[PDB]
Amino acid sequence: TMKVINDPIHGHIELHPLLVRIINTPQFQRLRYIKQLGGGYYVFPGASHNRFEHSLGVGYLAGCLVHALGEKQPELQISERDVLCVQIAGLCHDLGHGPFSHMFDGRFIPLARPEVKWTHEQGSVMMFEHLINSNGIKPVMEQYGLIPEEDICFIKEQIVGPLLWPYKGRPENKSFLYEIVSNKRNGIDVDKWDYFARDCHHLGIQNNFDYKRFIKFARVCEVDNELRICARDKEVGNLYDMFHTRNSLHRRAYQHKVGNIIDTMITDAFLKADDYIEITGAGGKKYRISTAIDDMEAYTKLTDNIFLEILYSTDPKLKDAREILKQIEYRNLFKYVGETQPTGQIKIKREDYESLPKEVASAKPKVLLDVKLKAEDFIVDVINMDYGMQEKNPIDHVSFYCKTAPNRAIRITKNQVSQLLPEKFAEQLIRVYCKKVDRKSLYAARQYFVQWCADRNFTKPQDGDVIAPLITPQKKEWN
Amino acid sequence: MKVINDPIHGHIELHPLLVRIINTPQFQRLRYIKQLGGGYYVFPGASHNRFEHSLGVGYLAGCLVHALGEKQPELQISERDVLCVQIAGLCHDLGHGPFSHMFDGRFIPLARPEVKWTHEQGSVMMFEHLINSNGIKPVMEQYGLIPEEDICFIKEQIVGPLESLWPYKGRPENKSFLYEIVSNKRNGIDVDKWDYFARDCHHLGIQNNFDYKRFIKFARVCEVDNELRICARDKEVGNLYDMFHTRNSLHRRAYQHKVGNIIDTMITDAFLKADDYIEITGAGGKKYRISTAIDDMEAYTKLTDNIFLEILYSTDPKLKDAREILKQIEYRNLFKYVGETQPTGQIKIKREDYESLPKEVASAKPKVLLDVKLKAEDFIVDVINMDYGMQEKNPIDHVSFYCKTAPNRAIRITKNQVSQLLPEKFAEQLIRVYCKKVDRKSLYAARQYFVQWCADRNFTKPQDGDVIAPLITPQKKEWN
Amino acid sequence: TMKVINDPIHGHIELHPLLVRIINTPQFQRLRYIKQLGGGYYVFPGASHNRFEHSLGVGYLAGCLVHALGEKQPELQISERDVLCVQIAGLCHDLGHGPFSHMFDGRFIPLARPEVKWTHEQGSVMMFEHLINSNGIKPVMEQYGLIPEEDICFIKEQIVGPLESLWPYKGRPENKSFLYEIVSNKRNGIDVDKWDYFARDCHHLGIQNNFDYKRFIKFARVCEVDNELRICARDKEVGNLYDMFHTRNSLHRRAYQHKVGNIIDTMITDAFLKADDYIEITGAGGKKYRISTAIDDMEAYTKLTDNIFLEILYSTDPKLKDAREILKQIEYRNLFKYVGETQPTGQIKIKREDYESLPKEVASAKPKVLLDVKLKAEDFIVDVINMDYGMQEKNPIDHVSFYCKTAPNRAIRITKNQVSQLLPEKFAEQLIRVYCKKVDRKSLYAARQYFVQWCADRNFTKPQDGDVIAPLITPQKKEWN
Amino acid sequence: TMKVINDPIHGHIELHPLLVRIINTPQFQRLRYIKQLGGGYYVFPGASHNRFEHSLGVGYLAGCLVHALGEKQPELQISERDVLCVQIAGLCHDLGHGPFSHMFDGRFIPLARPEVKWTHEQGSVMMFEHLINSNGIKPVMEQYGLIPEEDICFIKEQIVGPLELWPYKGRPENKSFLYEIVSNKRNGIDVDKWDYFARDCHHLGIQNNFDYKRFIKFARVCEVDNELRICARDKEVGNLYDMFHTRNSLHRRAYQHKVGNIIDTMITDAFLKADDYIEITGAGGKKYRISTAIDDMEAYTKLTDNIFLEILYSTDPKLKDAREILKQIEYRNLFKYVGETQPTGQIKIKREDYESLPKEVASAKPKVLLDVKLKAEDFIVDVINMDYGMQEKNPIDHVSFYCKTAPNRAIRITKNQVSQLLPEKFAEQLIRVYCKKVDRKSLYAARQYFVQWCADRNFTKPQDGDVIAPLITPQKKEWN
Ligand SMILES: Nc1nc2c(ncn2[C@H]2C[C@H](O)[C@@H](COP(=O)(O)NP(=O)(O)OP(=O)(O)O)O2)c(=O)[nH]1
Ligand SMILES: Nc1nc2c(ncn2[C@H]2C[C@H](O)[C@@H](COP(=O)(O)NP(=O)(O)OP(=O)(O)O)O2)c(=O)[nH]1
Ligand SMILES: Nc1nc2c(ncn2[C@H]2C[C@H](O)[C@@H](COP(=O)(O)NP(=O)(O)OP(=O)(O)O)O2)c(=O)[nH]1
Ligand SMILES: Nc1nc2c(ncn2[C@H]2C[C@H](O)[C@@H](COP(=O)(O)NP(=O)(O)OP(=O)(O)O)O2)c(=O)[nH]1
Ligand SMILES: [Fe+3]
Ligand SMILES: [Fe+3]
Ligand SMILES: [Fe+3]
Ligand SMILES: [Fe+3]
């Protein structure tokens, strides 16, 4: 029989025995100890939720969508084998997230090991392999009609994309299965649908996107010699609103100015603790926090725990790291100075991020300062907000259908929908903080910042006339 | 105090004066007017009526004014001011007609083109009638109000000024912020909106993305141009753009739903046909029609959604034309939706031209063999202005903000200071075409006329255009 | 294709073309103009919701449960024909409700026409027949694989029970008895009508619902019980099932039997009785029917809705002046005043026959207190209310079959003692509410004295507020100290 | 100014600067790392929520109730000092919970240190003292008008009851009602309950049937036996019985879930085995064990749910026994549930006898002479007392009520005055038996021992009893 489990977002989920068997392993249960929104918990006290339950929900929704397409269109010949594989992918899709989720792959690893190009997804594939092998799942897969050679490839391919038709796991006549868990074409996937619903529930924000409705009007059609998922013509509006909702959650919560500074402070403490923390891996080899990603037996033991390990330690080697985390407890965080954006079409390249604190201190504001501030006193956090496809409109990469001809796929441009939609689909936000907390240094920091904005032809800080009233009239373009 | 349980706002407390206003025919009337008119016939959850919206707006008006008072005693907001703001909120939609916006938005403009009449003007008149016919003036005095000054203040909250120095007679400039609570003429950020977002969502089955409670926590009165106004905190600017997005989104999904609108036009049509033969007893026994009941409030008190069922259940042969339209709604033989389109460039369609557009669609000569020719009376063309509440203007350019560092110093925040992902324009037009002939052959023809008419006037390609009229869409160079 | 419709309780419901065809008729759309909770709207301003949308939801849930049983147990051979019939029943199950729902079949018709035994359900069967015939549905049923002879009986049987020991149903055999337990469960009362209105009424009332129907469906299963295939719940759900009936009783206490909701219902009923004689409703062949007699002809009853309230209120006919004055008194909020509530003791049931006589008894009490005003029996209203777990004095859980994880085809019983000592001792009781038609301060004082005395006289329970409202009368009774 | 914080249950809470200052300390932030429902997370995957946010909410609701009583009844002379103190108590009320909340004070400490009588509350008082002293809060309290001598006593008294006629030193008899807000010793109706109902439901995926906001609207202080207490309105008596029903229902479904409890016993077991070899640095560097950290608050500050993962991730061979239990939880090789039963008549099982019950189950001689024999160490018998918070008493008999007609006159309402459908008793016991041997053969045996043991002690028939032990159930005359 089936196992039932009660998620507060999705209700009573049914779990196939194979899924239960995958779930009840150290590699998966690990996700109970990794928070979804990392440092966001330290701003939204509701956001205690962990990857474990996100992972169940993505598994659940993956099943819903593939099973729905099957009932509506038997011609597709979606097998119970295909359904199980899609569920397993959904279930295991975030297996490779590190401590504090996106803080790890987004802030820490890029600083700790700049040579590597590593992502949460690559980790998931590796950790999935480790889960299968270390728990004897392959026999159980066979028992329930799967073919490990073909299907383990298919599952991995659903997660990271491909390791003519680039996939070895399934033929072109089932390409639509690759658009369920992680949609490379346009980004409309069930990972999104779950975390919108889930993050909102815990954050204390209401979610404006109806995934259930999208499933009712979803359908597979032929597009360029390939069978893809298509939405109904009328849903085009709701799809633009899906990406709006996403961007809106990033603005309010995920990229919250203090959430991000807590993430940078935790990252900083990890960098300082890196050298002196050992994690036992395969064959007893010792791995560091930054190197545990190379061996999955070590990475299985690397969770949010590492924060409290550092905090509670008495090792004097970890004193520098422990002091940063103690400063978070007491709430002596680095102070937020302000936010700004580039103008024209000036993109700030990732290569230049290291240099920006130097530039802020280098500004010469025509105002008498109490204190001079060095470049090490500033932090400059650059954030790319987009609709998931850098500068592109993802709706231009969605296929639609009409009531009158439901097998005939079509495109819908932006002009066909509304003039009130966004003009661009990507931008950059630049947040500046100051490590010196006191009244005198904060005043100075504000002057350096608002000047630096004028110097580089950036947008006027929203509060700019208040924080630096002597600097804002200097720029002709701001009047 | 009386407590009452609204499913949106919880247990509301009602002041005795409010209870006394509520328990009158003029107010209880609102129990029999649906919030979303014809929308009930598309969203079966939307059974909710104006009565309960009216209570909630009254409630939120109290919340906001009471909150400003606690946070800023310097404003000297009196318990008299609070009561007046509550009364305005409570009575703000008193003048809605049968099926709410269908009445002031479709019916009255067709039935009586000479008049410029709104739900709000009706509210002021109906408020006056409520006060006089129920002896409220003594009760207002009993609770510290001054009817001369305050009844003006209440009416002014609802419709704006009753006639660039200070236009209000009800309160001085040092209390201008009170006029921004119930119906905000400056920018549109008011508690009417906050209630109906929450309420309509609850009943529609859509989730609401706007947190009014949060906005209240970061609201504050500051001096702006020699006048005390409500200001939001700098950080809320994003949430305010999202407020108007939420609004526009509710209009797109629900309020301007293609079938909701066609049901509204069909009910309006049946009212126009029934107008002449329905009498409503007014003041001194005078007889008023549906279209003329707005002139006398004793008559208008008896004009509700009932009028639909009165027509439907009637046996008078004079009402047969009207009754047949309403019977066609029951059976679901609605006028068929052909498609939607928009103008291009910045070519605005003037209101004067709306009458002429069915003629233009029939006048199109599509290069396709048609089974049926269709006359202009067979088409309906519904033009809809979607905006952020201030025609072509960005309402956030008319909001004052404040910073944590200087909370009495008001500032402005432009669009460029916030995000490049915000809208370029703040108004547009949608043109929906329907066909009165329902059959398979006429609908095909209608689609050809429509998609041609779109090409003829350099409008946008209908989303489904390549499917419904595949022989017409390649004709236009601009659509390839 | 399917039609999709967005209910705020259940989400996006799919409607089969046959159902759409049934929905889009005057007989069904009528339900848009009948409120679910009748006079409750005048106490809970959220409760604007109408039968129409309840009806859609019951149709939806009926589909969910039958479709779920089918997937989990193919051996049952549940056909797409069976599924459609169960949906149609669910959809049409409340078709026969009158103006203000339960006020009509529960208060008005019993007073207006005491000779008749009539219910909302009997009306539904009749109105279903009328819907089918007047809209040519029978051809459409055949088109989608139904057999009108057999299936229209099956649908009617789902609604009212048997149209009349052996197997009592003609619509389906004993090997599909479980289908009769979905829409209206005669065995124990666990049905999808309940599940929808809990969720729906709560949503609109502003009360939260403590019952998870989705969960019950996941652990539902058909087993053999006494040579008959019935729905069974899992052993562990027994607690949640007792809580289902608790939730029901709790909704009745808070909302449905609210003291003022009920007085508004009696006042509207009263106004209908006074308007009855002078309101004509055109029926079949032009014949004239009254409000009380429209139940006899469905073409008339199709036009009888909540409208009738506003028809009376807005009228100028002097024949309707008595009725119109009652409804105007509701607008102004001059309602009959609530005096208090009480219960019988021991095991003294008050028979329905005696309800007429109780106002006489209250006025007949001789309270040992100086009164300014004497009150006659016509001044009092006494409303008697039977609260139960749906099966008069019986525990409905004693009529539920259960199954275990270890043996899922073997049905069992679970007694009350096996579950908890904190469950109810009895499963039915009576509440007696007394109101006074005279509103003034002096008459209300008097009414309270008559009432609290009458309670002592008949060995009823002490009113909760009794020591306050009648402090000179409560020490008189030895049993209350 | 005020700090705003967004809790998903209560909305945007305002935090007074003094509260912020208390919140931002190691002793308080500690609560971020303790789960509300301990091992329940391993059954309800929604239940990730921690004490931190419960603590904020209780602080919030404490403010709501005291501030509401103040507005409705100025005669009480509730000061802004009183309000702050009530908030601080609410905020700090669960400061002393251990790893996995109630598992610690309810299972672990009673086994690890049977000599001691220790509770989460006693810990809170001690941890509150430590918080104040180690963070220099006393100056800040004074700055905002508090008097540390009197008020720190008042706060502690709100949490644990009297620290030693009128038993309280923190406030006089004319403010006794303040002691009924955070932790109500009289009847149990407090805001701790109100928060966790709402919160646990939100995260569990169960809906909550209790309206705390409504209760506040109809709450009021009256004189009762020469003392000013909180009273509810007469009509709320039903909703109050339903409050305790809701509580009992949450215990049945979630908190005392058969597997949640077995995971709690397994974690407790692993803690007992790890106790001796885990050192936690305390005050002056002294070494404390898990069981002894309760004696020194500097040590206890570092004792959180972490300790689970510390054991799990360790390589010390001294911790191998403990680490193996926790690894068995990961793999889901939990001790197997055999069944549940209750006593009959009025046979209470005394706490003294709990140790002996596994012996009794193995000692049963079922007449199906068994192919594997099981020893007493193979069985776990978990006894659970379900009540309405006051052992065998009806807590509604300890609530004072008032009537609309005389709102200062307090009264009592008995059970008979309300309903015959209420509970007969207000306490009972549940006995769950599990078996440590997991295999098919031992589980069969365990079931026979159990169902016999039930017959032997005249307990209730297990629900599944006829299925699991069909040879044993006809033996007992009383079960047919
Ligand atoms: N909504 C709700 N969820 C519940 C309830 N009880 C448990 N859950 C949640 C907790 C879990 O998330 C899920 C399963 O709990 P079980 O139904 O008790 N199933 P298990 O494996 O214990 O027993 P078996 O092997 O006997 O089937 O439902 C309840 O009454 N209500
Ligand atoms: N959530 C909830 N709302 C309720 C409940 N009971 C009533 N309401 C709703 C219905 C209404 O919206 C509101 C008032 O109903 P009452 O508090 O019962 N007040 P009334 O005027 O009858 O009592 P009096 O004159 O004796 O003061 O509460 C309940 O138990 N729960
Ligand atoms: N949640 C939600 N409900 C919606 C939305 N739009 C409509 N509804 C609700 C209202 C209705 O209950 C239902 C159907 O609305 P349509 O999807 O517009 N379908 P119709 O028959 O008009 O179009 P066709 O024949 O072209 O498919 O969904 C929306 O964006 N969101
Ligand atoms: N619903 C909602 N909650 C939000 C939002 N933004 C933050 N929160 C939540 C997160 C927090 O729980 C709370 C406050 O976050 P901030 O209002 O951003 N205040 P902070 O102290 O950063 O700014 P300052 O010191 O300048 O006043 O609201 C939002 O847009 N919406
Ligand atoms: Fe994910
Ligand atoms: Fe309004
Ligand atoms: Fe029903
Ligand atoms: Fe607590």
Image (spheres, coloured by chain):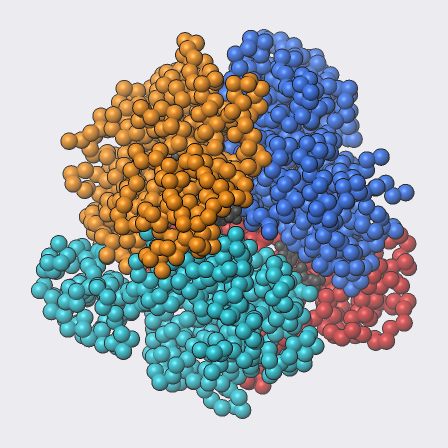
Chain colours: A orange, B cyan, C red, D blue
The number of numbered badges drawn on the structure is 0
Q: Residue at x 62, y 64 (%)?
A: B74
| Quarter occupied by residue D359 | top right
Q: Which is nearer the eye, D451 or B167?
A: B167
Left or right, C262 with reference to A96: right
Residue C378, above or below D1: below
Instruction: Name the spot of residue D465 as percent of width and height, x first.
Output: 61, 25
Instruction: Name the spot of residue C422 as percent of width and height, x first.
Output: 70, 38
Furthest-front residue in view? A368
| Quarter occupied by residue C418 | top right
Q: Which is nearer the eye, A446 or A48?
A: A446
Q: Residue at x 27, y 30 (%)?
A: A161
Instruction: Name the spot of residue B294 as percent of width and height, x first.
Output: 45, 82
Q: Residue at x 48, y 69 (%)?
A: B225
Residue B62, above or below B403: below
Left or right, C181 with reference to B370: right
